[PDB]
Amino acid sequence: MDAFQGILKFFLNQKTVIGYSFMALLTVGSERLFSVVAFKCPCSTENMTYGLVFLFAPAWVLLILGFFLNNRSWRLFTGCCVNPRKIFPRGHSCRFFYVLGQITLSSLVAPVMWLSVALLNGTFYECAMSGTRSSGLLELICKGKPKECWEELHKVSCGKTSMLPTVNEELKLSLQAQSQILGWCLICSASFFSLLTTCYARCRSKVSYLQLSFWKTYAQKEKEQLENTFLDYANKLSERNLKCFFENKRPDPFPMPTFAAWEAASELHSFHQSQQHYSTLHRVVDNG
Amino acid sequence: MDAFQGILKFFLNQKTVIGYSFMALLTVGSERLFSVVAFKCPCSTENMTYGLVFLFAPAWVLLILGFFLNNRSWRLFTGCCVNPRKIFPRGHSCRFFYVLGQITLSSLVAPVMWLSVALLNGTFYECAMSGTRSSGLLELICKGKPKECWEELHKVSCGKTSMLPTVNEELKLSLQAQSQILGWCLICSASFFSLLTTCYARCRSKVSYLQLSFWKTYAQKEKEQLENTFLDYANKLSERNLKCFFENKRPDPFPMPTFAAWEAASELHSFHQSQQHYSTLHRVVDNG
Amino acid sequence: MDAFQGILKFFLNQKTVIGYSFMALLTVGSERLFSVVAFKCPCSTENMTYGLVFLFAPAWVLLILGFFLNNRSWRLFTGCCVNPRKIFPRGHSCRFFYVLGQITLSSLVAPVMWLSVALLNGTFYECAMSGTRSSGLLELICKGKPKECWEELHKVSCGKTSMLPTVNEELKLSLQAQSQILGWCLICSASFFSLLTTCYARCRSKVSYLQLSFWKTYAQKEKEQLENTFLDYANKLSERNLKCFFENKRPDPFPMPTFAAWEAASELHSFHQSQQHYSTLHRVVDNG
Amino acid sequence: MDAFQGILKFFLNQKTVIGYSFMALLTVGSERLFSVVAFKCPCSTENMTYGLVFLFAPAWVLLILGFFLNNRSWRLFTGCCVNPRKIFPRGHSCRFFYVLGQITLSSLVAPVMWLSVALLNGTFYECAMSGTRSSGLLELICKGKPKECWEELHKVSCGKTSMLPTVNEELKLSLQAQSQILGWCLICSASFFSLLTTCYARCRSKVSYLQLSFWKTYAQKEKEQLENTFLDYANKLSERNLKCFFENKRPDPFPMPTFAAWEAASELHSFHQSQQHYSTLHRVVDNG
C-alpha cells in the first residue's frame, strides 16, 4: 500500500539525475554500434576526412536536436517580429543573452558525451591521425621507427604493410592511447566548467534559498492550472459555436482577454525585490 | 491506480517524437532487408541504372504515400473547381503557397530518412559508381592503380577480375567510404534546414506563445465536438426517413444549414488581431 | 501484515550504511570494466602519462559530482553576493569554514573508494611505474636483474623483450605487489582519519546526546511541513491570478512575507544554550 | 494464522545468535575471494611485508567499523568537553573504564573471526613465513633438507627452484600446517576468554536475575516511547513556527525543558539498591 507510495517520492525528487544517466547510457550503446557494424577504415588518402566525420557529425545532429526539444526556446522566440522590443526591455537590456546562453549550454551536454565516448574507444582517431601529412606531429609518432614510417603510416589500420608486422602492432597502440588521454581531458574540463558557471549563477541570484524554493513551486503549477483553464474555456467556446451553426441562431457575447492583454502576459520575467512578483502573469494582474 | 494515469500523461505529451522515432526504426529494418535478400549487383554495363533505382524509387513511393495520409491536403482541395476564389482570397493571395509548402516539407521527411540509411550502408552507391563511364570522377578512383582500372572497374563488386585480388579489396573500401561521407552530409544539412524554416515560421507569427497555446487547444477539441454533432444529427435524420417509408407518412421539416453556410465554414483561416477569431467557423458565427 | 511493517523500520533506521555499501559495490563493478575492456597498456615512452590518467581522472569526476548532489552546498551559497556578511556573522566568524570543511570531507568518500579498488587491482600502477626514468626507485626494482633492466623496463607489460622470459614474469609480480601494499595503506589511513574527525566533532558539541536527538527529529520534519505549506500557498496564488485575467477583474490583496523576512530566515544557524532555538526559522519567530 | 505468529517469537528471542552466525558466514565468503582472485604471492624479498598486510589490515578496518556502528559509543562521548566531570562522577570514578572496556571487547569479535579464517586457509602465512631471514625458526623448517634450504626458501610458492621438485611439495605442506595449528589456538583461547569475562561481570552484578530481567524490559521500551514523544512534540513545534511566519503573527509560549534538565538526563547510569532507579531519567524525575 504505502510501500509503493514511498519509493516514487524518492524517484520523482531525483529526476534530473536519471535523465542524465539515461542520456549517457544511450550514447555508449550507440557508439558501440557505429564502430562495430558500420565503421571500417579505408587505407587511402581520404583517411583524415573519413575519421573526422564519424566523430563530429553525430555531435552536430545532437546539438540541433536539443534546440527542438527545449521548451523555453519557443517560449522566447514566438511572435518576435511583431514587436522586437518586448524581448529587449530598456531596463534590462542584457537578459536576452542570459536566456540565450542558457539554451546553448543546456543542449551541449549530449554533444560532449558523444565526443568523450568516441575518444575513449580510439577507432575514429586512429583512422584520422594516420592521414596527417604534416611536418609536425609526425616526428612524435615516428620516433624510433624505420625509414618507411613517413609514407606508409596511413596503411597501419588494415595491416598490408611491408614493415616487419610487429612494428605495425605497436604503432596502433601508440595511437589508441593518444585518444584515450584526450578523451579524459574532455570529461575533466567540461565537468569543472559546468560547476563553475552553475555556482556563479546561484551566487549572483537576487533571492535566497528559501524564496527560490517557493518560486520553483509556483512556476510548476502555474502551468498545470493554465492547462485546465485553457481546456475548460475551449469546451465552452466550441459548444457555443456549434449550436449557433446548426440552429441558425445569434450568439451571446463571449468575454475573452484582449490582444493587448495577451501580449503583455508573454514578456520575459525578471525579479524585482521592491515589488516581489513570481511570474509575468502575476505582474500584469497586480498592476493592470 | 494513479501510477498508470501518470505515465500516459508523459507519453501523450511527447507524441511527436515517438512517431518520428518509429518512422526511423522502420526505415532501418526495411533497408537491411533489400540489400541482404533482394539486391545482388550484376557486373555489366547496366550498373548505373540498377543501383540508382534501388536508391531513388523507394523514396518516390514514400513521398506520394505522405500525401495520402496528410489530412490537411484533402481539407484544402475538396471542392476546388466549384469556386476557385475561396482558396485564393483577395486579401491574402499568398497563403495558398504557405499551406502547400507546409504539405510538401512535412512529407519530405521519410524520403530523406531513406536516402540517409541507404547511403550509410554503401552497397547501392558502390554498384552505381562502378559503371560511371565518365572522364571526370574516374581519375579520382583510379589514382595509384594499374592500367586496367579504367575498363575493369564495373566488375569489382563480383570479384572476377585478373587484377591481383588485393587491389580489388582496396577499391571496394574506397567506394564504400565515399557514400558514408555523403550520407552524413545529407543528415547534417537537412537537420539544419528543418530548424531554419521552423524558427522562421514561429518568429514571424501573429500571436505570442500564450495565445498560440489556446489556439491549439481550441482547434483540437473543435474536431472532437464536430464528430459528436455530426453523429447526433445523423441518428435523427435516418430515423425520420425510415418511419415515413414503411408507414407511408408525410414527414416533419428538418432544419439544416443551407448550401451558402456549408461553403462559408470551409474556407481557409487566417488570423486577424483586430477581431480575434480562432477558426473559420468562429468567424461565420460572430459575423453571419 | 505486520511482518512487512517490521522490517522496513530496521531498514530505514540503518540507512546511512546501505548508501555507502551501494557506493562501494558500484565502484568495484566500474573498475573491473575499465581495466578489462578499455585499458591496454602501450609499451612506449608515454607509459607514465597513460597509467596516471586512468587513476586520478575518474577520481576528479567523482569529486565534482559530489558537490552537485550535496543539498547543503546550494543552501549556503545561493544569494551570496547580495549581502556577503550574512554568511560571515561577526559573532561567529569561523563557522563558514566548518560548514565548507563538512562539504569537502563528505564528497571525498567516492574518490577514496576509487583509488583503493584501482590499487588493489594492480594494472594501472604496473603500466605507470614501468616508465619511471628516475635514478631513485629504479635500483629497487632492478636489484638482482641483468644489465638490460634499466632500459627495457617499459616493455615488460607487452612481453616483447629479449631478457629470458621468466624474468619478465617475476618483474610483473614485483610491481603487482607494490600497488596492493599501497592500496591497503590508503584504506587503513582514511578509515582512521574519518573516525578521528567525527569523534572530535561530537566531543566538542554544545548539546548532549538527548537534546541532539530532538534536534535531528525537528530538522527532518520542518522540511516536510515546509513542502506542504509552499504547495498550499501556491495553489491559492495561481487560482487568484487566473480568475482576474480571464474575467478582467481586480484582485483582493494577498498577504505574503516581505523581502526582509525572507532573507532573515535563510541565515546560517548556530546553537546558543542561553536561548535554545533549533532552527533559524525558530529564532526569527521567537524574536521578530 | 497463528503458525506465522509462533515462529517469529522463537526467532526474535534468539536474535543475538543469528547476528553472530551471519557475521561469521560473511567473513568466510570474503576470505575465499581475497585469496582466490586477488592474492598471488611474489617470490621476492618483499615476502614478509606482502603476507603480513593481507592478514592484519582487513582486521584493522573491521575494528574501526565496529566503533562507528556501536550506538552506545556516541551516547557516552557527545558533549564531552562542555563539562568533563559528568562522565567522571566522584562517587563512581571507575565506571568510565568499565563502559569503555565494554565498547572495545564488543568490537573485537569481527577482527578475531577474520584472523581465524585467514589462518585456517594457510595461504597468507606461507607467503610471509618464507621470507623470515632469521637465525631461529629457520632450522625448524630446514631440518632434514638440503644445503640450499637456507637461501631458496622464499621461492617455494612459485616453484622455480632447482631443489628436486618433490621437496618443494613437502615444504609447502609443512608451512600450510603450522598456520592451521595457530588458527585453532586462536579460536580456543578467545572462546575461553569471552566466557571468563562475561561470567565475571554477571557474578559481580548488583541485582539478581529477576530484577535484571525487568531492567532490560524497561530500557528497551523507554527508547520506543522516547521516539514517539520526540515525533509528537516536533510536529507541534513546526506547525507553530510556520503559521507565525506566513501570517506575521506573534506566537504563544511553548513549554520545553530547560538546558539544565537536558544535561542532567544525559549522565551515566549506575544502580543503587537503596533507591532503585532503572534509568537516569527515572532518577531525575523522582528527585528533581
Image: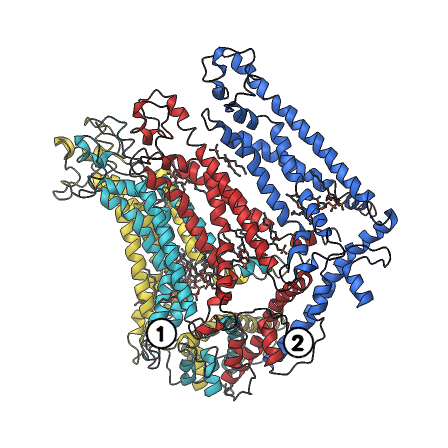
Chain colours: A cyan, B yellow, C red, D blue
Task: Tell whether label 2 touches label 1 (CB within 8 Å).
Answer: no
Residue extending furthest toward the bottom: C250
Q: Count the marks: how many? A: 2
Amino acid type at image mark 2: Arg
Q: Residue at x 59, y 62 (%)?
A: B5
Q: Nearer the viewer, mark 1 or mark 2?
A: 2
Disc 1 with disc 2 on a shared chain: no
Mark 1–mark 2 Cα distance, whole angstroms, equals 41 Å
Q: Residue at x 17, y 39 (%)?
A: B141
Question: In the shown orientation, is residue D195 left or right of residue A98?
Answer: right
Amino acid type at image mark 1: Arg
Q: Nearer the viewer, residue B274 or C138?
A: C138
Looking at the image, is D49 positioned above or below residue C235? above
Mark number displayed over residue A95: 1
- The location of residue A41, given as percent across then percent down, is 28, 39
Q: Quadrant of the C terminus of chain C?
A: bottom right
Q: Residue at x 47, y 59 (%)?
A: C68
Q: Chain of mark 1?
A: A
- The location of residue D281, given as percent across then percent down, is 77, 62
Confirm whether residue B241 shows in the render.
Answer: no
Question: In the shown orientation, is residue D175 left or right of residue B146?
Answer: right
Question: Badge 2 is on which residue?
Answer: D240
- Please identify the quarter of the rendering in which residue C13 is found: bottom right
- The location of residue B190, given as percent across then percent down, is 30, 57
Looking at the image, is D206 positioned above or below residue A131? below
For label 2, the crowd category at 10 Å Cα-Cα, with few meaning under 14, some 14 to 19 and many 20 or more, is: some
Q: Secondary structure at mark 2?
A: helix
